[PDB]
Amino acid sequence: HHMKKLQIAVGIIRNPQGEIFITQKLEFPGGKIESDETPEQALIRELQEEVGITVTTSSLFDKLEYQFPDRHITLWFFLVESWQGEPWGKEGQPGRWMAGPTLDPAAFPPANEPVISKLIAQ
Ligand SMILES: [Mg+2]
Protein backbone atom coordinates (compact mmCIF):
# COMPACT_ATOMS: atom_id res chain seq x y z
CA HIS A 1 0.00 0.00 0.00
CA HIS A 2 2.75 2.48 0.92
CA MET A 3 3.22 4.65 -2.15
CA LYS A 4 6.82 4.60 -3.39
CA LYS A 5 8.49 7.86 -4.41
CA LEU A 6 11.27 7.80 -7.00
CA GLN A 7 13.22 10.64 -8.62
CA ILE A 8 15.48 10.22 -11.66
CA ALA A 9 17.94 12.57 -13.39
CA VAL A 10 18.58 11.99 -17.10
CA GLY A 11 21.03 13.67 -19.48
CA ILE A 12 20.35 15.00 -22.97
CA ILE A 13 23.93 15.08 -24.25
CA ARG A 14 23.92 17.23 -27.40
CA ASN A 15 27.00 18.09 -29.44
CA PRO A 16 27.29 21.25 -31.56
CA GLN A 17 26.17 19.28 -34.63
CA GLY A 18 22.78 18.70 -32.97
CA GLU A 19 23.36 14.99 -32.32
CA ILE A 20 22.24 13.39 -29.05
CA PHE A 21 24.12 10.54 -27.38
CA ILE A 22 21.47 7.82 -27.01
CA THR A 23 21.99 4.48 -25.24
CA GLN A 24 20.07 1.20 -25.41
CA LYS A 25 14.27 0.55 -26.22
CA LEU A 26 16.42 3.68 -26.54
CA GLU A 27 17.02 5.89 -23.54
CA PHE A 28 18.93 8.83 -22.22
CA PRO A 29 21.64 7.98 -19.69
CA GLY A 30 20.90 8.84 -16.09
CA GLY A 31 19.57 7.30 -12.92
CA LYS A 32 18.14 7.61 -9.43
CA ILE A 33 18.56 10.81 -7.42
CA GLU A 34 19.59 9.79 -3.93
CA SER A 35 17.75 11.38 -1.03
CA ASP A 36 20.69 13.58 0.03
CA GLU A 37 21.55 15.13 -3.34
CA THR A 38 20.30 17.57 -5.95
CA PRO A 39 19.05 16.36 -9.34
CA GLU A 40 22.18 17.74 -10.99
CA GLN A 41 24.51 16.00 -8.51
CA ALA A 42 22.87 12.71 -9.47
CA LEU A 43 23.09 13.63 -13.16
CA ILE A 44 26.83 14.29 -12.88
CA ARG A 45 27.51 11.02 -11.09
CA GLU A 46 25.24 8.91 -13.28
CA LEU A 47 26.64 10.30 -16.54
CA GLN A 48 30.19 9.65 -15.32
CA GLU A 49 29.26 6.05 -14.48
CA GLU A 50 27.14 5.29 -17.53
CA VAL A 51 28.83 7.13 -20.41
CA GLY A 52 32.16 8.27 -18.96
CA ILE A 53 31.78 12.06 -19.24
CA THR A 54 32.08 14.73 -16.56
CA VAL A 55 29.24 17.22 -16.97
CA THR A 56 30.67 20.76 -17.19
CA THR A 57 27.42 22.74 -17.38
CA SER A 58 23.78 21.70 -17.60
CA SER A 59 20.37 23.30 -17.77
CA LEU A 60 17.01 21.85 -16.85
CA PHE A 61 15.24 20.83 -20.05
CA ASP A 62 12.00 19.45 -18.63
CA LYS A 63 10.70 18.04 -15.36
CA LEU A 64 8.00 15.37 -15.65
CA GLU A 65 5.95 13.95 -12.80
CA TYR A 66 4.18 10.61 -13.25
CA GLN A 67 1.50 9.42 -10.82
CA PHE A 68 0.75 5.70 -10.73
CA PRO A 69 -1.56 3.81 -8.32
CA ASP A 70 1.48 2.48 -6.42
CA ARG A 71 4.28 4.99 -6.98
CA HIS A 72 5.15 8.56 -7.96
CA ILE A 73 8.07 9.08 -10.38
CA THR A 74 9.80 12.40 -11.09
CA LEU A 75 12.07 12.60 -14.15
CA TRP A 76 14.42 15.57 -14.39
CA PHE A 77 15.82 15.97 -17.93
CA PHE A 78 19.00 18.05 -18.19
CA LEU A 79 20.42 19.48 -21.38
CA VAL A 80 24.19 18.87 -21.36
CA GLU A 81 26.12 20.76 -24.03
CA SER A 82 29.47 21.11 -22.22
CA TRP A 83 31.37 18.16 -20.80
CA GLN A 84 34.75 16.49 -20.39
CA GLY A 85 35.37 13.18 -22.12
CA GLU A 86 33.95 11.26 -25.07
CA PRO A 87 30.63 9.43 -24.42
CA TRP A 88 30.66 5.66 -24.75
CA GLY A 89 28.81 2.68 -23.34
CA LYS A 90 30.83 2.61 -20.12
CA GLU A 91 28.49 0.06 -18.51
CA GLY A 92 28.74 -2.36 -21.44
CA GLN A 93 25.53 -0.96 -23.06
CA PRO A 94 25.13 0.38 -26.61
CA GLY A 95 25.46 4.11 -27.20
CA ARG A 96 25.58 6.31 -30.30
CA TRP A 97 25.06 9.82 -31.61
CA MET A 98 21.62 10.33 -33.14
CA ALA A 99 20.57 13.44 -35.05
CA GLY A 100 18.11 15.36 -32.89
CA PRO A 101 15.52 16.15 -35.59
CA THR A 102 15.14 12.44 -36.41
CA LEU A 103 14.48 10.84 -33.01
CA ASP A 104 11.49 8.49 -32.92
CA PRO A 105 9.43 8.95 -29.73
CA ALA A 106 8.03 5.44 -30.22
CA ALA A 107 11.59 4.08 -29.92
CA PHE A 108 11.86 5.45 -26.35
CA PRO A 109 9.81 4.47 -23.30
CA PRO A 110 6.62 6.57 -23.42
CA ALA A 111 7.66 8.41 -20.25
CA ASN A 112 10.15 10.30 -22.45
CA GLU A 113 7.54 11.26 -25.07
CA PRO A 114 7.12 14.98 -24.18
CA VAL A 115 10.89 15.45 -24.15
CA ILE A 116 11.48 13.67 -27.48
CA SER A 117 8.73 15.79 -29.05
CA LYS A 118 10.48 18.98 -27.91
CA LEU A 119 13.91 17.81 -29.04
CA ILE A 120 12.64 17.25 -32.59
CA ALA A 121 11.52 20.88 -32.81
CA GLN A 122 14.92 22.17 -31.66
MG1 LIG B 1 22.81 4.25 -13.33
Image (cartoon, grey):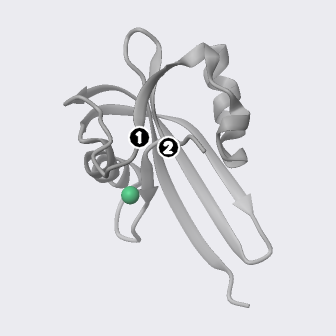
In percent of width and height, residue 98 lies at 50, 21
Which residue in the rendered view is the most extreme toward the left? 84
In percent of width and height, residue 1 lies at 73, 91
Q: Which mark is residue 94?
A: 1
In the rendered image, the vertical position of residue 1 relative to residue 48, given as above or below: below
Residue in view at x 62 percent, y 78 percent: 4
Residue in view at x 47 percent, y 45 percent: 10
Residue in view at x 80 percent, y 75 percent: 69
In contact (CB < 8 Å): disc 2 and disc 1: yes
- Under tag 1, what secondary structure? loop
- Under tag 2, what secondary structure? loop
Residue in view at x 31 percent, y 42 percent: 51
Q: Amino acid at mark 1?
A: Pro
Depth order, front residue of 89/43: 89
Looking at the rendered image, the quarter that the C terminus falls into is: top right
In the rendered image, the vertical position of residue 93 relative to residue 59, given as above or below: below
Residue pointed to by mark 2: 24
Classify mark 1 as within 8 Å of ligand 1 or not, answering yes or no: no
Which residue in the rendered view is the most extreme toward the right? 69
Q: Amino acid at mark 2?
A: Gln
Q: In the picture provided, is 88 more to the left or to the right than 8?
A: left
Which residue in the rendered view is the most extreme toward the top? 17
State which image quarter holds ligand 1. Answer: bottom left
Classify mark 2 as within 8 Å of ligand 1 or not, answering yes or no: no
In percent of width and height, residue 42 lies at 36, 55
In the rendered image, the vertical position of residue 81 relative to residue 90, given as above or below: above
Q: In the picture provided, is 116 more to the left or to the right than 32?
A: right
